[PDB]
Length: 92
Length: 92
Length: 92
Length: 92
Image 1 (cartoon, rainbow over the protein chains, first blue to last red):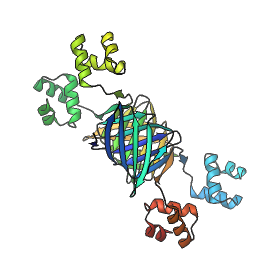
Image 2 (cartoon, rainbow over the protein chains, first blue to last red):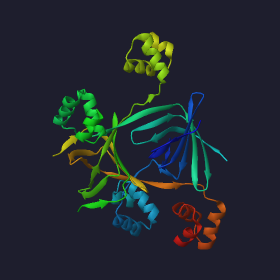
Image 3 (cartoon, each protein chain N blue to C red):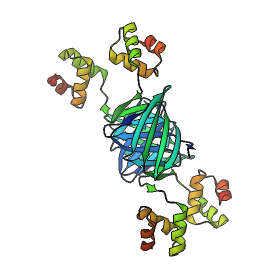
Image 4 (cartoon, one colour):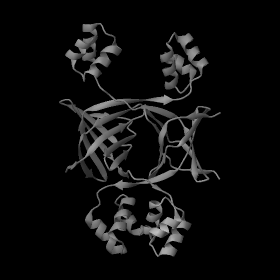
């Protein structure tokens, strides 16, 4: 027996390396043999669990101009050294 | 047209008043007409969510003395109505 | 310099034993001396991190009637034994 | 009229496209006219959120060949527009 589940703000699916989030989903429920089955329908988004500190443009531009590094590498290097310019430079 | 989704540690279903948590569920996925549908099977547990707020002592007292309610119920009533005294009284 | 932060769906404050969730908050930001300060305003709710399995009324009522336990104790006992009636009974 | 909030392990600020995470922040709280205001200070990091969906190969190919975009950008463009090809093309 399928039943509608009202007022669901969000479903989150958690894995080791990431989470999947469905906002304001449509959700149905069923109970069978001791387990519940939930059908969740909506648009999903993927949350990679790594977070990165922000880096100022001037610092990125400086490192690029001084080392010949790409924007990608300069940015990464500065994240890798906690925003320390001298060490980002040294590392490139 | 279902695919298996491997390594799911937890699914949480979030509503205003509570969340439903399924540990180490089995999860299937399909996409149809722009929406994902996830089927999630496992044993479910519930976790309730309560209004987080400051309740004036004098309001708790007033509700208790006017309805004969315990401190516990008066406090929960006022939480339920967002500190509205008239409604807290009416519900008890 | 205070700046408004638009489109914030939710702020979650995490502690060891619980989380505080503010839905669709108003949020302002300021940067000073390397740290950002966020002012978050809205109605909060408290998520206690313990989740409980559901228990059928018939089982609660049975245990109550057979042991003389209160609804609170019968419910707790059945959660404590994973819904096993014979052991809930034995425990009361 | 601020109180200290002790033992906060993390604050997460959630938006559609990203989340801002502050580890071991300092947090103050006050209540005024029915709303809580939280002040949260600490070093912030960003975590981006991406549309989770199936993108047809032939659509990726079409966008690449029509705009000269890399597989990477075409795929991200189509993610950005929810699989709408016209708009994916226009944005690249």
